[PDB]
Structure formats: C-alpha cells, structure tokens
Length: 440
Ligand SMILES: *[C@@H]1O[C@H](CO)[C@@H](O[C@@H]2O[C@H](CO)[C@@H](O)[C@H](O)[C@H]2NC(C)=O)[C@H](O)[C@H]1NC(C)=O
Ligand SMILES: [Mg+2]
Image (cartoon, rainbow, N blue to C red; front, top):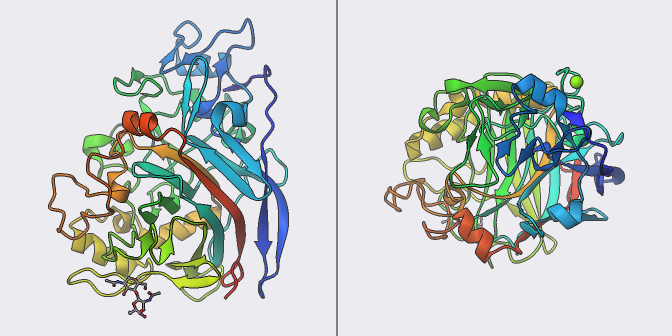
C-alpha cells in the first residue's frame, strides 16, 4: 500500500514507564497508531476509493500487486472518526463511533517507539509488564484487549517492496487467528477470491491470512478475563493460505494455535474471583501485572512460567488457583498446566504441539509489538470469554463455563445497537524487571 497525503497522520501521544530494580520508574514519550485496515484507501488523485465497505474497485485493483501500487492509506481523524483519544498516560478506546455516512465499530492500535515511525519492540522474557484498566463500560459480548504480537518493527516496510506505508500507517498486523480479513498482507492487496461478508457489511476475506506468535496478556470485559499465550510453527509475520490459515473447519490444521493455553479464573473453577464486586473488582480501575519467568531467572533462560498479580485499592492480589476436578492446583501458566488443562477440558493441545512456552519465549526474544483494541466477535459472540462455550455442551462439563453472560449475548448487531457507548481505558503502562512495576 502507498501513502495517502490528503490528511496528515499524527499519532496520539501516550506516556508510558520504564522501571528499574527497586521500583524506580521513569516516564517515556510514546504514542499510538491506528491499524491500516480501518484507514481510508484511495488513489494518489484523481481521488477514487480502492475500497469501500467490504468491496474493492476492480479497475484499480485488477490483481494484488497493481492494487498495492495504485492504492494509498491516508491519515486518521482519531477521536472524531475512530473514537480513540489519549490523555497523559491513559488511552480511551470507544466501541461505536457514528458518522454522517458510516459507523465505526471497534479499533485496534499499536504502541509506537520513541521515533514515532516504527513500533516499540518489547523483549518480554525475564520481564514484568503492568498496566491499569477500567472495564466498567465493557459489558457481555465486548473485549478490551491488551496483547503482544510478533509484528515487524516497521510493519513490513523493508520486507515488502510494494508496502511503502509501513508502521507509520499501522500495516503488517498478524496474530494466531491468521486473519484473512486483512486488506494488505506482504505488500499485496488480499483480493484473490475476495468474498464480501454476508453478515458484516464492514468486512470481507481474501485468500490469504496473516499469522504470527501472540501473547494475549488481557482479553476481558466487566464479567470475565483470560490471559493466553498462543504459538505458531513460523517465526514472525507470515502469510498463509489454504489449510495453513486454519480457517473455520480446519481450525486445528493450520500453522498457529487458535485456542491458546488460556487462564480464565472463572473457567479454571473460581467464579468469585474477578467481576463486579468480586476480589478483583471490575466496577473500578485496577492494575494487571504479568511476569514472564525463565528457567534460571535470566534473559537467556527458556520461558517457563507466566505469572499474574493484580493491584487494587492499594492491595496486591495473588492470582486465583485452579479448581478443576482431577486437575492439580496451578495459579500460573506452565507447559505442565497447559498439558493438564487441555486434557481436563478435552481440548486439542495445539499450544504444546506447536512448541509451547519455549516457542513463545523465542518470539519474545525476536521482539513483540504492543496492541490495544476494543472489539465484538463475529465468529463466536465473545461466548468463549464470558459465557458457556460451546453452547451445545453441558454447562457443568469442566471448561465449558467461562462466565455468567447468556449464550444469546454478544451478537455484534445486537451489542452495536444496544451498547454503542461502551469503552475501555488502558493507562499507566509499565515495563521492567520482575517485581519492579508495582508496590508491594
Ligand atoms: C477463589 O479465589 C479466592 C482468592 O484467592 C479464594 O479466597 C481465598 O481463600 C483462601 C483459602 O485458600 C484464603 O486464604 C482467603 O480467605 C481468601 N482470600 C481472599 C483474598 O479472599 C477462594 O477460596 C477461591 N475459590 C475457590 C472455589 O477456590
Ligand atoms: Mg516497502
């Protein structure tokens, strides 16, 4: 994709922190960028859209390469068009942003580095990541996500000749769902066999998907939360097609683990731990601390454990323990835990099959990009996060019940109509050595 020059691109500023052993943190000038899929896409000018709604202009895009060559991503009106705003160290992502001719649903942004051109690269092994979240405005069917993906620092600028836009315009997204809704993958328009969605006027899918390792630190709404590593048998952002994308029917055939090895306190058998008025009280702001422990506690150790702590109202809250029949007590993610839970829940252990935490830590060594988003789920209505899933399964079968939301909740059309003013606020982002990001 080329660079559109109709509208200046200015990344909303966001202050984050870097912490040292002992607890001293310093502030850092960073910013956020909107994912390229949301952007206006058009010719150099004479200005005609290359894409609108869920269809392409076939004259400008007769093939993937010509399309990338002809088509330019433009600047974004962050607050007024996309409902994205920042104040100090806080990012607000609004769910539905109405306009005269269209409605914007959700958003996805990436944290920019100090240079405001390339994405910030995080090296998470032997490190701790903290942030504060307010989910009071995220009901059933919504997801305020903070996570990491193995994107290129330049979003594909240097790798792909016909990507001339790069990270400044939020290109190069990938994750373990290997999304095929992505418009540009590998500097080529994803138009081969393009199918406009019959149930979503904003989305289509092409032949290709964009896959990479993903650490889901936080997928949550007021009701429930999950922390979930996912791995792939490929290194970095990789284009897939056919069975490798593991689309729908061939979910467990592809190159990435779509389910991931998840820790949802409610799913792991503690229904009183997290939610409105619970131990971690989702009616108010709280801190989420995530520690990435290695085998020998060095930066070259194998990633061996992912621990979680919360901090609310000045109190440090230890993660809940698993409470599943036949299953041992774990309060953290280890390869051992992953084997145990996939077995206990009768799930395909793709996480371990594709190399488990070792492979995840190797992604961390290469480097990962920080993603923040708000979204609804056109695939499974967010039921996997906050309800009973599969809906056809017994609600008392271990692993089925993930939250208190109704199996009829989270239909996109319904939540967009009924809960348009939903929002998530992520704030006070911190990175440093284990034990440095929070006060005991
Ligand atoms: C769900 O998690 C909470 C929080 O850890 C548990 O409540 C604690 O129970 C332990 C006993 O192991 C005691 O130390 C405390 O009284 C509780 N702590 C707090 C902060 O309330 C609760 O037991 C868990 N529920 C289940 C079913 O395992
Ligand atoms: Mg290029």
